[PDB]
Image (tube, coloured by chain):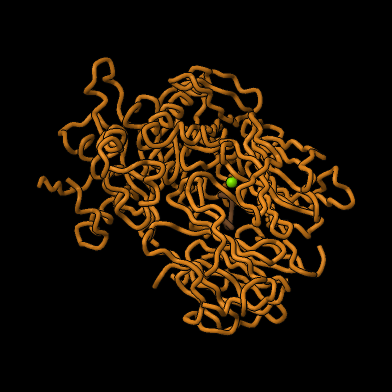
Amino acid sequence: YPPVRRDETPYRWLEDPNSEETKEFVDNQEKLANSVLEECELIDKFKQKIIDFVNFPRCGVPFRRANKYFHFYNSGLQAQNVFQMQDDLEVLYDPNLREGGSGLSLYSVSEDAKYFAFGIHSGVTIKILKTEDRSYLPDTLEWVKFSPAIWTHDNKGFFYCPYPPNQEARYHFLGTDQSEDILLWRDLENPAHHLKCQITDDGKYFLLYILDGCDDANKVYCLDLTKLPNGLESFAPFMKLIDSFDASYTAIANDGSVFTFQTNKDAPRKKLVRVDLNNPSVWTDLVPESKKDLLESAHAVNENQLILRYLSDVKHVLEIRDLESGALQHRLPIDIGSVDGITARRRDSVVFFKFTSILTPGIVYQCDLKNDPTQLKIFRESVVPDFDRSEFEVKQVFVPSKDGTKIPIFIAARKGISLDGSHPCEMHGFGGFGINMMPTFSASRIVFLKHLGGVFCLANIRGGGEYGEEWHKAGFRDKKQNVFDDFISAAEYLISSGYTKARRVAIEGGSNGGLLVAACINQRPDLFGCAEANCGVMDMLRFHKFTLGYLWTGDYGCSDKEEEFKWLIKYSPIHNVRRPWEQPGNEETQYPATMILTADHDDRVVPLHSFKLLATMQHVLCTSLEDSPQKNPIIARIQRKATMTQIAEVADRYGFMAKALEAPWI
Amino acid sequence: NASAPV
Ligand SMILES: [Mg+2]
């Protein structure tokens, strides 16, 4: 282990990325990592198996503009998905030709299908090309992050929500410099409010949603585009339908001024409501809140219908309903997995979506609502080469947390294995921000299952949004600790039930999921054989200061206030490193072999989090003693600055895991 | 738009 300087007046200095001492600190930990990974002889064998299982063709869900359909395609191992078009159900843009692949993050086709606006990481910048001949327009727009490009129905330009060179809502006309873009909204009073936006399917209304923090609540402003004196060239006169942060609202459809909205107002599991803009105080349930299932999303389709995607004990259910009445017309349950990517719009009569699952790589279903609304027909099916899925099975069980609450978890494993404790086990989780963790497809997970005899578990802990807003709130702010408790209880069940045994269990997560993993190792290190935390939040007292971690106080709180500081100090990972051997009746326990993963250019979760936690752990556990009991290594894998890049990382983590758990190859 | 489900 290398030398790390503890500033007693300890690792505040790592918060500066560019000093020598930090950049040499990196190199030493890079240097140490590779030395460790060199000992994990199964890295290469995993790496090749991942590549062989990922090598299958994948189609994105298609969408229609005018007479044309568009979709992403990948032949198997291309760096980045390629965007294609066709005349019925051709390359349009191939990012593998730029830098040998960054992918497209923005992609947006005009209503007439003439123009394709898209965005690349120039090191997000939006460009536009003509679909007829693939020639570029000159228009270049910078300072975009996650805003889409929303085309007006005149095909003359589009809305987008850039930051300054204080988020703004702007309109760009085709064939102008970005400096001529109309400013539609900003708020210097509330620099932290951020924006999402949308245009109604009929083209009459531009909708602007304002949000405060990552909380699921938003304002709703409506600009009627048909009542502008000289269109958007004026400058705006928003109708402020909702001007507070009390509930969430998302527009699903409108008939003239009569709008249908999804909301969580007085409805933690969500519902569809109806309001007339011309009479704004009268809201009426259209599809009431289910007291059982989360209404996750809704989409108007085939002129007069609706498709509701419900989440019901962490499985999807799709309902077809009448738009005007709200009446149930059909209900299609979905096997364990996830459907999503429903991009069909109100004047589309064929609906497409994607189904993936732990043992199912990707199916694009097509429901023609005109002709055969009953059955899902397969449009595309991906097949994992050399893999027979009927030797495996996934099942769901519910497990009691500390406080009594049920925690649903999925368990993927080989069929008919004896529950004898002898199987290596990987547990994933996230638990935060109302994010739903679905059991989707991962090729590396298959390698683990087949070539390591592994058992995999996905834990739907609190903090997520799986049982609605109550599930969320029961795992945020003062209640964050429950999330960690849920996860620990999940491992305990895997042990007691006899899938695996303490120290034969690995855990992995990213971002908040990184927090999750860091928190749990401190509190219960005797449980785990291996921990892997991908760019987590590890400094809970200071996270808010950097880049855009300020929009997570909604879910975490903040040290600034005292009541909150006291939740935080209790689980903040760097401030909770302790020698588990220095505790009574706990002496053969050490920390699991740990791998902290992070980039150099992640300006979401800044890497200081990861670095400071590494510094601390190596100190308290290893180098702070002369003959530390901590034998298990504590390293970082740092990604200097794409399919193959992403495969390398995972191959490493899995090789490390296999070493850590003494899992042999099969 | 992930390139691969790794
Ligand atoms: Mg909503």
Q: Quadrant of the N terminus of chain A?
A: top left
Q: Quadrant of the C terminus of chain A?
A: top right
Q: Residue furthest top?
A: A585
Horizontal and vertical percent position of residue A663: 47, 32
Horizontal and vertical percent position of residue A264: 57, 41
- For this view, does A570 lie left or right of residue A316? left
Q: How many marks?
A: 0
Q: Is residue A461 above or below residue A224?
A: above
Horizontal and vertical percent position of residue A479: 40, 31
**What residue is shown at x 75% (from left), y 48% (from top)?**
A306
Whether residue A37 can be seen here: no
**What residue is shown at x 33% (from left), y 28% (from top)?**
A523
| Chain A display color | orange
Q: Nearer the viewer, residue A191 or A665?
A: A191
- For this view, does A80 lie left or right of residue A59? left
Q: Residue furthest right?
A: A371
Whether residue A586 can be seen here: yes
Q: Nearer the viewer, residue A597 or A325?
A: A325
Horizontal and vertical percent position of residue A331: 78, 37
| Chain B display color | brown
**What residue is shown at x 49% (from left), y 59% (from top)?**
A195
Q: Nearer the viewer, residue A199 or A294?
A: A199
**What residue is shown at x 15% (from left), y 49% (from top)?**
A5
- For this view, does A249 lie left or right of residue A61? left
